[PDB]
Length: 342
Ligand SMILES: CN(CCN1C[C@H](CCCNC(=N)N)N(CCCC2CCCCC2)C1=N)CCn1ccnc1N
Ligand SMILES: NC1=NC[C@H](Cc2ccccc2)N1
Image (cartoon, rainbow, N blue to C red; front, side, top):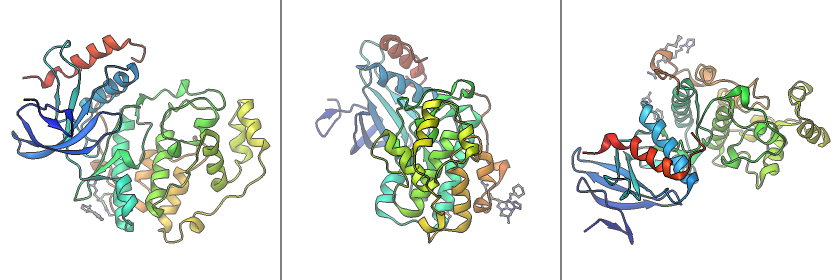
């Protein structure tokens, strides 16, 4: 009786039919489906997180943020399907707009025109402006978290690693463990930052811009410290100004121990790129997070002037935990999903 898909249970009630397997990957399993009430095809993601406290924490964060945000460039939650009781609730199904591809899949197979790069970048920054205006950090921006439909609308997804910004509590020691995807990590993550300031998102967007220009990751480090050495290989040795900002001795002395390296010019790395795009790239991939361009300045950059319109770049109406045993986490997920029950 319950709907089955390639061997596993995927019972999304009577409303969602004609399921088609889309993917998997620890985060449960995704299928497209038909929404008999709105008669559009939707995407449905099955989540089975309750067996691990980390999965429940990320599930709760994503649900709470996505339910509060409302923005054209941020994926919404259309519906949440779960059992009527906490005892019977083993999985949760998240219903979202159906998006045909993501930037990761697209960069694997397609070359982007400069007009596409410009428009995709504009929508990323437009969505990020709203996120940061809510005092939220995404913390895992990368091509696979940017969804695209057939008319080139872009929507940011996957807020499971998000945090509320906390700049006064950002400092930490050298080579401190971190969770977000290595290739998109800002250099200060490896040096002295917990990733609690808005500048770590801007770095990631700069990495995404570089990748849209070349179809390959600009800093493809194979391990934690290898990441920093890739960044320094292109940006060159940090200046005295930038090093005086790093007061932790272990991090400072690591950088001082390296042979001097000169900056590789962006136009050597991206010889086909719009020069205005490379000027913005340079400002987003600035070593010093305090000198790095902010989202509202990036939107106002000449590269984006055919789209820039601050009156059409909305902000959140209000600014926006992690110690809970999985049982009250399940209880919190149950409460947060109650509004979708019949
Ligand atoms: C030749 N124009 C660019 C073309 N565009 C695009 C834009 C509409 C895009 C819709 N996008 C959306 N999301 N709805 N618009 C009206 C927005 C006013 C601007 C200019 C004054 C300051 C506030 C922003 C334009 N005139 C250059 C303008 N200009 C001069 C100095 N600096 C800039 N940007
Ligand atoms: N403003 C604006 N609405 C639609 C159109 C989208 C687009 C897509 C690819 C390349 C350029 C532009 N542009």
